[PDB]
Image (tube, rainbow, N blue to C red; front, side):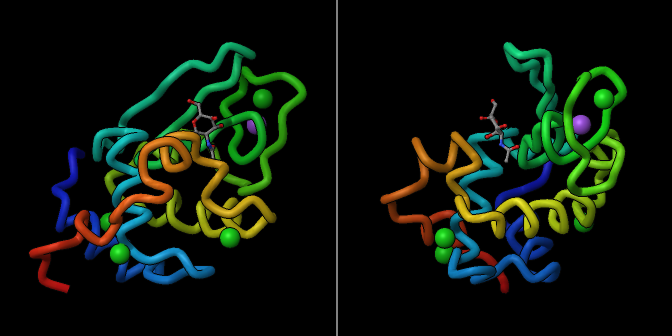
Length: 129
Ligand SMILES: CC(=O)N[C@@H]1[C@@H](O)[C@H](O)[C@@H](CO)O[C@@H]1O
Ligand SMILES: [Cl-]
Ligand SMILES: [Cl-]
Ligand SMILES: [Cl-]
Ligand SMILES: [Cl-]
Ligand code: NA
């Protein structure tokens, strides 16, 4: 599923991502835009053999299990395919644990390089929330 800008913002707000650990809703929509282009089925191969999955490109090296990343962790206790669903519930709940381990949203490289320090509210402007 390819989310719309306002459609994803409302789904993220309903799942409690607005101001979660001090990160306004514009940060999560901006991150999902530059990580997956609002595509829930987006996957990308990392150089170390791990794979990023879903709307937020959650890596399999730590958070999910895909069966081919040897020596990795499954900290979110989910199959990585559950992150590719049109229901972003699994990706949201796992992102809440990732953003809470100390580094915040810096765990998403796209957010650090393309959203951090910018006007993130412009990603939710004009949306019925
Ligand atoms: C929280 C999370 O899984 N972040 C990943 C990270 O593993 C990696 O640096 C990158 C790979 O392209 O994409 C995402 O930012
Ligand atoms: Cl915002
Ligand atoms: Cl594995
Ligand atoms: Cl949803
Ligand atoms: Cl933080
Ligand atoms: Na894993």
